[PDB]
Image: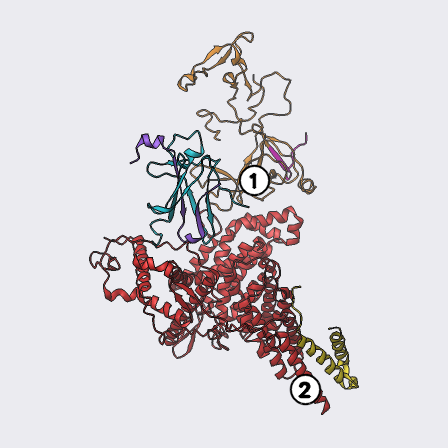
Chain colours: A orange, B cyan, C red, D yellow, E purple
Amino acid sequence: ESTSNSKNVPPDLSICTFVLEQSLSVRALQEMLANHRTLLYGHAILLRHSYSGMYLCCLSTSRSSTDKLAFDVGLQEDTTGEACWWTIHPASKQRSEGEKVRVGDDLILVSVSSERYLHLSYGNGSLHVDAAFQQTLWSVAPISSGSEAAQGYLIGGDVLRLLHGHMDECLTVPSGEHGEEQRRTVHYEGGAVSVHARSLWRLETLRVAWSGSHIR
Amino acid sequence: PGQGRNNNGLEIGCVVDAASGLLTFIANGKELSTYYQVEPSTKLFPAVFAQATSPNVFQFELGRIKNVMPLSAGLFKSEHKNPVPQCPPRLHVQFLS
Amino acid sequence: NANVVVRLLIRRPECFGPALRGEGGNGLLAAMEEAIKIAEDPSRDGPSPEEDDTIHMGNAIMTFYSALIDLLGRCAPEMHLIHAGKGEAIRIRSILRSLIPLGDLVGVISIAFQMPTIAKDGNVVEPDMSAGFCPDHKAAMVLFLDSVYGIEVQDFLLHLLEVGFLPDLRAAASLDTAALSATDMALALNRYLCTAVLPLLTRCAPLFAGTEHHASLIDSLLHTVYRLSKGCSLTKAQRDSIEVCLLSICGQLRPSMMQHLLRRLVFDVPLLNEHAKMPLKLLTNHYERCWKYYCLPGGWGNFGAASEEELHLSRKLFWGIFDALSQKKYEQELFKLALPCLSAVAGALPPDYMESNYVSMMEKQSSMDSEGNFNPQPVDTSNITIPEKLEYFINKYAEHSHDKWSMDKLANGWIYGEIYSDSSKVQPLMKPYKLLSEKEKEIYRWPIKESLKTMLAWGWRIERTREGDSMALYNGYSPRAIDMSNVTLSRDLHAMAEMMAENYHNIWAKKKKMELESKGGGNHPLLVPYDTLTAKEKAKDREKAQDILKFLQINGYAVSRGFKDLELDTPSIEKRFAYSFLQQLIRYVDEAHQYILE
Amino acid sequence: CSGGHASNKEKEMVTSLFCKLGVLVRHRISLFGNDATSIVNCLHILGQT
Amino acid sequence: RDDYDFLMQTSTYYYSVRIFPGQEPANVWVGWIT
C-alpha cells in the first residue's frame, strides 16, 4: 500500500498494522518447536495481523512471478510451525546481533521456514512482496504503544459513531434504499442506526508514524 | 439381419400398453414377432440380463417414440401427463445379489 | 559444511548460471538441450578465429551444470535426519527441491545419447565425449534425484524407468559386439549404469512388488539387465552390481512375470559356463520363493498356478541342468551352485506332472539363437495358398482399412479428391473403395493376404458360421466407421493376437536387419525381441493384429487354433516327472554300484 | 488332498532305490570317505518315504 | 408427428435399451420382470 501519496490517496493502515506477539531467541524457538520484552537483533519474532488476527508467514505455495525461486508471503491461522516466525537482523554495520532494536533502524527479515528474505520484487508491472533470496531493507515504524490510556481517550485508527445529541441521532448515510449514487449523502438519523454498521466512521490521521496515538 | 452396428448400437425398445396389458418389442424400427399379454394390476420392472463381453454394456434410454409416453410418466404420478422424458434420482439401477 | 555452502549459494544466486537464476532464465532441461545444440554448432562450440587449446563450450556448460547439481545433491541432508524431522535438514531439503524441479531431472535423464556406429570397410565411428553429452552428466542427475526427491512411489519409479533408465540399459546392451563394447561410450555407459542406475533400482526393489499391470516394461528391464550381464568388457564390480540388481528385482516380482526370463535361461544355464552362475542363483531363489506357485494345484492364492508352459520350462531346466552336470567335469563353485538349483526345481515341480502331449506347433525358439539372441525368422507364407472362400472378407477388410485411412486423411484436412491435385496435396484422390482403380487394390489388400496366409501356416481354422454369416453375405464419399474400439477379444484370442504382433515385428526386424547389413552399420533400437520391447513400442503391431482379429470376429469368421489331443496320454507309469526322475536315479545308482564293483 | 498319490510302480521304484543304496553302503563307508553321512542320510529319508 | 390428444390420453409407455457395439447381443436379454 502506497504511503508517499497520502496527500492524494489516503493509505489503508488498518490492514497494514501488525503486532509483535513474541520475540523468542533462535535456540529457544527451535527447542519449543521440538517440544514487555525489548526486541533484540537476531531474535525470531511473531507478527500478528491486527485486523484479521492471522499471522505473517512464508507460504509454501508460490505463484512464481517469473522468479521460479521465490515463495509467496501471506497469512495463516495456525501459529504452530516455523512458517510464522521471522528472524530480525541489522541492515548496516553500525548495529550487530544482540543489540536492542531502535525505532528508526532498518531491519532485514529472514523466514525461519525457508531462509528467504522478505523481498520486494519489481518483476511485475506492479510491485510484489515475496520470500526471495535477495535482501530488502524494511523499516519498522510504530503505530501504537502499550500505554492505551484508559478506556476512553480517542486514539488514531478508532472506529466510532458521531452522536449529535444525547445519544439522539447519529451521523450516517442512506443505506436501506439500496442505491450507490444516493449512499453518498450525509445526514443525522435516529433509531437502530445507532447499532447498525451504516453509521460507523474511522478516524485516520494524516501521519504514518504514530498514527494510533491519542487525538489532540 | 446381420449388420455392423456402426451407425448405431442395438436399440431394443420395450413398449407396454398398460390399458391392455400388452408387451411388445421393437428391434430397429420394426416390431418383433415376440409379444406378451400380462394380467391386470401386474407390476413390471424394466430389466436387462447381460453378460459382460465389453467394458460398456448398455444404456437404459428413458426416451420415447412416436405417440408413446416415456417410462417416467408411468413411474411417477406427478409426471403422468408430461411427455418430456425424465430420469429422477429415485429411479436407479438395481442388480441381483 | 553442506548447510554453510547451501546458504552461501542461495545468498549469491548468480552462482547457478544463466539458467536456474530466475528472472527469465530457462530450466535445467532447456539449458542442457541448448548446450547440446551449441556443441553441435561449430560456430559457438569452438573459438573460430589431448584437449590442447580446444574447450568445447557446449561440453563446458554441460559439465558446469552437472557439477552444480552433483554438489547440491551431495549437500542434501541424510535420510536419518529427515526421518528424525530436524528443522534445518527439512528446510535445506525444501530449498533444494524448490531450486530444482523434478521434471527437469527426469527430462535430463530422458535425454538420449550418441552411439558409436559401424561404417563401411567395417570401421568404428565413435563421437567424441569432449564435445558431447556424457553419462556423467546424468550420473549427477540421478544422485540429486535420489538425495533430494528420492524414489518412494511405484508410479514414479516405473515412469522414470520407462523414460530415462530403460532406454539407456537397452542402449548399453546393444553395444555388446567386439568392436563396440571396447569403445568409449559403451565403457562410460557401463560405469554410469552399474554405479548410479542399478544400485538405485536395487534400493527401490520393494516398489516392484505389485507391478502386475506393467509386465511389458518389467520384462524389458529384466531382459536388458540379463543381456548386459552376459556382455563382456565388464569389471567384477559391475558384474556384481548387475547380479544384485537382478536378484533383488526377481525376488519381489510375481511368479508369473519371470516366464520369459526363464525361457531365456533354459538356453544358457545348461551350458554351465562361467556366465551360468547368476542365472543358476536366480533359479534357486525363484524356485525356493515361488514353489507353491508350481507345486500346489491351487496356487499361491492371489498369484494362481502355472499355465503348464512354465511347468514344461521348469522340467526342461531340471533335465538340461541335470544332464549337463552329469556330462561335465567337476568344478567346485559350479557344482556347489548347481545342486541347490536342481533341488529347488525338483521341489517346485509336482511329482505327478504329466508331460504335455500338446506341444504347441512352431514355438519361437527360432526367433532367437545362441550368441545372437535375436534371429528374426518370419513364418513362411509363399508355399501356403489362400482359400477361395475368404475373398469376401478380403474385400470387406480392405474397404474398411481404406475407409479408416480416408477418415484419417480427412482429419488431416485434405479435401475430396475429385482430381489428382498433388500441388494442393489432394493427391490420394479420396474416392469410395469401389471407385478406386483396380491397380490400387493391392496397397490395401496385400497386408490382409500376408496376415491370412500367416494364420493359415500356423495351422489355424478361420471357420465361418452358417448362423452368423449367411444373412451377412445376403446383405460423394460418406465413409462409415466400424467402431471396433469396444469389441473385446477372448484370452486365447489375445494370445494369438500377441503371436501375430510378434510375427509382424519379426518381419519388420528381418527386413530392417537386411537393410542394416547392406548399409554396414547403424543399429536401430527396435532390433530387439518382442518380449524385450516395451508396450508403447509394441502398440502398433498389437493394434494391427487386434484389428484383424476383431474384424474377423465381427464378420463371424471364428479364428481357432483347432488342434485336438489324440489321446489323454495318462501313463502314470511313463509320463510322470517323478517316474522319469526315479528311473534315472535308479539307473545312476546301479551304475555307481557297478563302478564300485570293478 | 491337493497332490495325488504316488503310483504303485512309483513306490516300487522308491523301495528299489532304498535297497540299492543299502547294498552300496554295506561295508564301504571308509571307501566313501566323508560322504558316508550323506549316504546314510539318504537311506534314512528313503526309509521314511 | 405425434398428435397431442392421443399422446395425452394414451396409456402406452416406452423405454429402450441400447446394447453398445462390441458387446455380443446373444449374451444380453431385454424386457420386463415382476
Q: Is residue A93 above or below residue C34?
A: above
- Taking depth in this image into account, of C225 and C455 the one nearest to the observer is C455
Establish if C349 lies above or below A30. below
Nearest the eye: C235 or A18:
C235
What residue sits right under mark 1 in the picture? Answer: A58
* Residue A37 lies within the magenta run: yes
- Whether C116 is drawn above or below C2: the answer is below
Residue C54 is situated, as x and y percent measured from the top left of the image, at 44, 67
Q: How far, Cα to Cα, is label 1 from label 2?
A: 84 Å
Tag shown at residue C591:
2
Q: Secondary structure at mark 2?
A: helix
Give the number of marks: 2
Magenta stretch: give its range: A36-47
Number of other residues with Cα within 10 Å of mark 1, as a class: few under 14, some 14 to 19, many 20 or more = many
At label 2, counting other C-alpha atoms closer than 10 Å, the crowd grade (few under 14, some 14-19, many 20 or more) is few
Name the residue: 38% across, 72% down: C511
> Pointers 1 and 2 in contact (CB under 8 A)?
no
Return the chain for callout 2. C
